[PDB]
Amino acid sequence: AEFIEMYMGLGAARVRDLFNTARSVAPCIIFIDELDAVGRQRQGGGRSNDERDNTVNQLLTEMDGFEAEQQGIVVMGATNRKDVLDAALTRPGRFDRSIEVRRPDFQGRLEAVKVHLRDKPVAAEIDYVSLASLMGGMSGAQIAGVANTACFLASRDGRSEVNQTDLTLAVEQAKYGRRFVGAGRKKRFAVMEASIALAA
Amino acid sequence: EARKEGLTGVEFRDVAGLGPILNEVVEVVEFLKDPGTFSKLGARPPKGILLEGDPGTGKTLLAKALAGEAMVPFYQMSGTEFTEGIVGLGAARVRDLFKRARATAPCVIFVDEIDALGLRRAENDSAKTNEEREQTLNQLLTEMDGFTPDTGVVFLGATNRADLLDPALMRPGRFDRK
Image 1 (cartoon, helix red, strand yellow):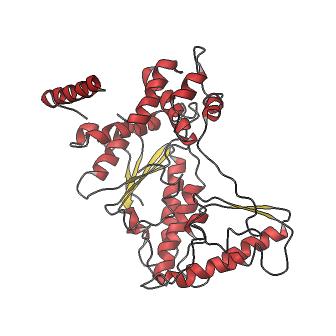
Image 2: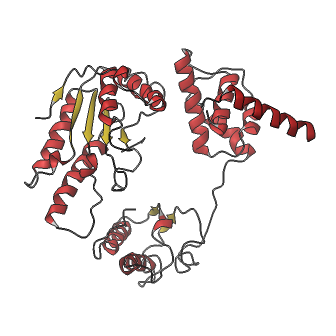
Image 3: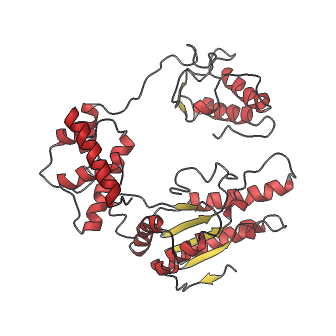
């Protein structure tokens, strides 16, 4: 996003200065976030394709380029989808290894539930396998969020930490969310779900 | 001088028709009243909050009510307040204002129609009119990017069109909530 600029010819300038400082302080590791928003495939398209394209071109001549190398510096990038970026970037020789970051598994959640409460007050009556199998499908940021929410609900309750029962409610309201429904529209819901249950 | 509203006298009865918003504001006013306990929470407060929506719904009617229920200094003024036509002085108003906040911490800083500062500058118009708006942009950029989370300086920002937003202030840590 720092390389996104609508002036004429400063994206390549930023790439060049970044890579020159990296070459000067070698060895190094150059991490670029938001790669999916600049390095999409080049096309005719609008007039941004006159400069946004040019920018990417600079990149294509730094990681491989001439001079045959700088040091062998490691470059890494944060993107969400490999298929959106063009074939010139993600080809081997410019990005050799491609590793994946999925959502936490059963083990990942098993250890992230406790690792997120090491710096958080909490009681003894907790079984981390229960919450590891109880909130499968959320991201790690969401585990941080549910821990934050349980702590804040403790704050609003007057206690400093939380037992099982209330952080379970916190995660369940982080899943299904927390509106008023009349008493005549409520019996319709009751009747239809009861009939579905009886059938199934 | 920015109008120093020491006492605002605004409560949550000074607002009506914003039930769902009432409960996300008590968090901010509790953080304003307790700047030392939220650091004990390990959580970080929202540095900036953007008041987005239709005009006439009560942005400053809510922001001033927030500062009143906090009982803490309130600093409101215009977004074009720093875009009057002399180069560089707009950076002084932002600097003076934010170090006023640093000196009277904890504080509230509010800027209605702030997008006049963060107007996404299109490539259709004048250039020196661009480096002054962008000058003040980078000025408050440095100002709040160098700030600490627990200084008690809560950043209030309001505008009635979120479509003209510049991506700079949308970054996390600059407007942690909307």
